Length: 107
Length: 107
Length: 107
Ligand SMILES: [Ca+2]
Ligand SMILES: [Ca+2]
Ligand SMILES: [Ca+2]
Ligand SMILES: [Fe+3]
Image (cartoon, rainbow over all chains, first blue to last red; front, side, top):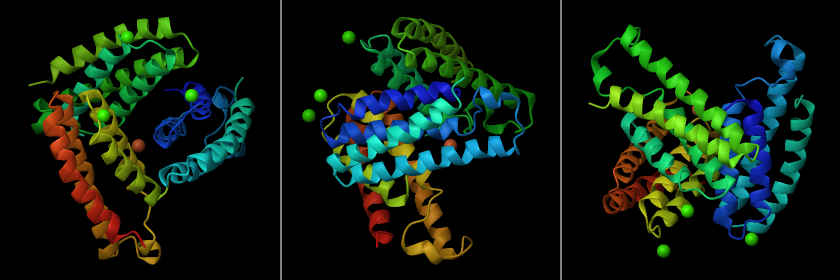
């Protein structure tokens, strides 16, 4: 998948987590979020199509994506421990990082 | 998973997409298809077991697998946008690329 | 996800496989197990936090993780062929490798 194809996957999975009832539904959706970032970190968003791979703007994008995989991993551990409530709470903060990263490179 | 283990995963997920009702069912199955190709592109099919990694026959296999991940990504974006109909239509063309690649290296 | 976050994912997915009714439920959970190992093989467990990357104890961990991905792949192929019974049987042996690896680096 390209960049925004996995970005929209993160957005939809956040909508699945907010309506998920058990911990298995939250965990599987969070792993789909981690998976969507596993193949999209290597892709390039539309705005940075003509930015150097060593350009600080393109470098910012990689690390901003690295925070995302880090927060997703923390919510996965909370959902893995059975804390379905605290994992959904961590998913609401994930929604902030996903939306901020998605709007900065949407164009 | 080995090569044909993920090939049969693509075939079964295509059967899940053709019977999927909502867009979330199509998107998750398509990401399972992208995931099945993410770890099987690095594996080697049975026929090419004794073919050089730089052999044009083995090289053909890698690129033919690269088309597959590209088509899967396009269907993921269609399913991510909510176009459950057009994503299923793209999945039927995916069935052509999966079956052609699966039969050429099945043996 | 970090190391134990994916370790607990393997444990929960084993509980999903033992209660899965059809072959698609077993296959998807097994691919979640393969996915959980795809990003956790590159992480480091708590005990080996201060062990050299070329240390035989840290080297043992990588190969012990490599057996895990190999067994998961074999159960995926059994579940892909439709053998839902034999794949669940392979999942019970997977439970031995997961639990042995999980307890050796849990601390
Ligand atoms: Ca609900
Ligand atoms: Ca149906
Ligand atoms: Ca049951
Ligand atoms: Fe990878």
